[PDB]
Amino acid sequence: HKKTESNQIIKTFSFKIKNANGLSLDVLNDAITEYQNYYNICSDWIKDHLTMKISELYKYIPNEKKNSGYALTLISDEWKDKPMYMMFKKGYPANNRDNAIYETLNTCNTEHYTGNILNFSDTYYRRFGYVASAISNYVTKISKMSTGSRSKNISNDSDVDTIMEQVIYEMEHNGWTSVKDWENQMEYLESKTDSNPNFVYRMTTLYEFYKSHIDEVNSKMETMSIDSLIKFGGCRRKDSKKSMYIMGGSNTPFDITQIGGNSLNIKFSKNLNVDVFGRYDVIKDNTLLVDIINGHGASFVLKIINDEIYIDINVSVPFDKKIATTNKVVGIDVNIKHMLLATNILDDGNVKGYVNIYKEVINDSDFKKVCNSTVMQYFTDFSKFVTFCPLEFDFLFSRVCNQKGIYNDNSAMEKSFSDVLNKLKWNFIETGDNTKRIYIENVMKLRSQMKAYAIVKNAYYKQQSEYDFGKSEEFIQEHPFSNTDKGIEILNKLDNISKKILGCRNNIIQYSYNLFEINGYDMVSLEKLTSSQFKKKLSKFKDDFFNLMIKSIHFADIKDYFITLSNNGTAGVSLVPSYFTSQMDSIDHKIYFVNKHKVRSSQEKHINGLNADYNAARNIAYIMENTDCRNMFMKQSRTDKSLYNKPSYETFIKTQGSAVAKLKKEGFVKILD
RNA sequence: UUGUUGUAACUCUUAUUUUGUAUGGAGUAAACAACUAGCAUCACCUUCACC
DNA sequence: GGTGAAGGTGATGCTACAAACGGTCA
DNA sequence: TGACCGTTTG
């Protein structure tokens, strides 16, 4: 837009306020409410005029600004006879759109802007903060607005209705309005050596169709878009997000200066003068770790969290991160049925800083006397390779049964395993080692908090059923269980438990990543779980337990924290396909298709002979440690952009069918019995 | 100990089966790890009332 | 099995300005 | 009058 980043990243730091010179909690809350009200009214105005001629807005510009650059574009022949939503597209000039819409809002004055509570100057608060925020939100809504034409695979060779639908999809989904931009994209595609002619045939055919069919395709696209936007509820602003955004001017006074005691003073314009506690990553012993003094942006955010006022200062900081080599790849099978992070590393006892819980659970005198043969075999198999956070779900359910009074088979080994974990925690407490003790306590706390989350969420469901029963539809649809006092208390408990679960999971992930860094590994591989693949469903309690507590750990987000760690770390993270890692044999690297997930049936083991989780981890590692398999499946990320929160390598496979078709061509297939 | 979050040890305390190996509360206490945030939209899942 | 509300997760997209003009007060 | 800083324009 107006800020450009080159080999750098914009980092936002939230600072807790202290000595707020008149910026009280109630006053800031009222100011935030007024800001949200103004934003909502402007969004409503944008909605009500969204399917309206652009050149009609020219009548709103004041006479003294008729010769302005942006006003001329309003009545220019290119956009003279187009609906207003067309300015929220790549073709239209962004700055002209912003200025023209701001002028229309100011002249119309659909909300009586008499001034805000905090007495910010009008330019920032109105023109730059909320009007610009609303315009940017409507841009991000309209730009990729899919009229409902679902893309289909059999592509060009079909009927004329197919041609129409696919041309609409291709013009819209990537945001095209003009033929010139489309021709520029075709030139870009033809410049690239990697043709991929299968899609190129479709692209060229629909380009040729669009060449001589502009009038009716434009008319039908406009009609479909208008139809979609009539029933659009508008970019409304939620009331549960207490926040306010301000943008300073080019010459505005916005100075941040140290005031001793690891504190900072923020002085913006003339109506803002506050002090902030500081942060351990920006200031350390009165010394600065980031160039916040002379690198901070001109925009800040005032927000309230837990009835505490924060201010967000964002700074452009250098970010030198490269793609990671693959001289030593670590595969991680993220399946949380038994453990949390399976790994393809054999545990020979020479992994520096690694504690194997499974190794010292099967070597515990008290545990041997209780665990049956099958579980003992499970734990002997797991202990042979590196693994993290033993998370036996049936064990948590047995604990739930113990609490609820229902007998369960695993009850004795529950106490046994917990006693082993506590013994490990105390051994590491007395030994003085910090990281291992942190890991052990995090595993124990996470195990307890998943059960707590399940209990509290089941109680939430039961209480919602109790309160909602026998009431009118209007009464419950306007006064839901979420916003009542009992509901808000329950959701507060849920949020606390969720935060603690996320914290323990992040600590475990960081421990694993530190282990990988110390051991000399260079690359980390995970499945690209775009969403929870297990998100679909007396034993109803067990099923709900398992499902909601899959959802609680942020099962698909576990990779995201791995990339977050890789940002400042020295090991890269890749997202490999999640369609066939659990089915590939790891000896000959082939696939059993004749597929079906029921391969892992014999005592939690694979037909190959190795353990199922170990097999999947080995497959995930192999996807990246072999050049051929990477080139087949794995596309290196763009090194010209920023690698912050971006994998070093990532898949271009979007469905199971494409993957299974891709395997067959080069081999990698076998037949089951 | 200069922010948020997760993780200790130690001394008390009702309360909580709407966190019973855990949490709220009071006191004390230290090292180690992460932290790009805001706003809007879309998709999906779950629960609940209804048929 | 869907229609509505709520909760949440996951993904996406804009955005975090630069330079010039003009009002005002020492 | 020049010098901050709120306002207007790409």
Image (cartoon, coloured by chain):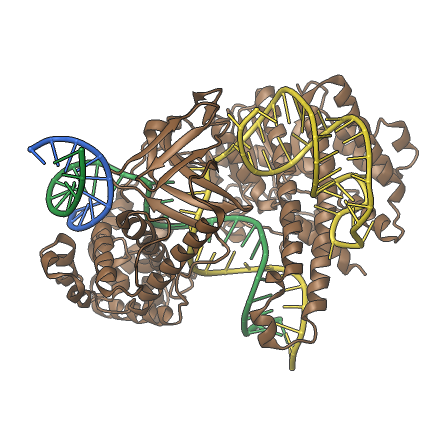
Chain colours: A brown, B yellow, C green, D blue
Q: Spot the residue most to the right.
A: A369
Q: Position of residue A406 (x, y in %)?
A: 88, 54
Q: Is residue A69 left or right of residue A209?
A: left
Q: Is residue A107 left or right of residue A572?
A: left
Identify the residue at horizontal 24%, vertical 70% (top origin). Answer: A216
The N terminus of chain A lies in which quarter of the figure? top left
Q: Is residue A163 above or below residue A581?
A: below
Q: Position of residue A497 (x, y in %)?
A: 66, 46
Q: Is residue A219 above or below residue A634?
A: below
Q: Is residue B29 left or right of residue A298?
A: right
Q: Position of residue A153 (x, y in %)?
A: 43, 59
User: Number of callouts in the render?
Assistant: 0
- Which of the 4 image quadrants contains residue A428? top right
Q: Position of residue A381 (x, y in %)?
A: 77, 33
Residue A651 seen anywhere in this rendered image of the structure: no
Q: Is residue A198 above or below residue B6?
A: below
- Which of the 4 image quadrants contains residue A619? top right
Nearest the eye: A534 or A191: A534
Nearest the eye: A287 or A643: A287
Residue A431 seen anywhere in this rendered image of the structure: yes
Identify the residue at horizontal 49%, vertical 34% (top origin). Answer: A628
Q: Is residue D8 left or right of residue A446?
A: left
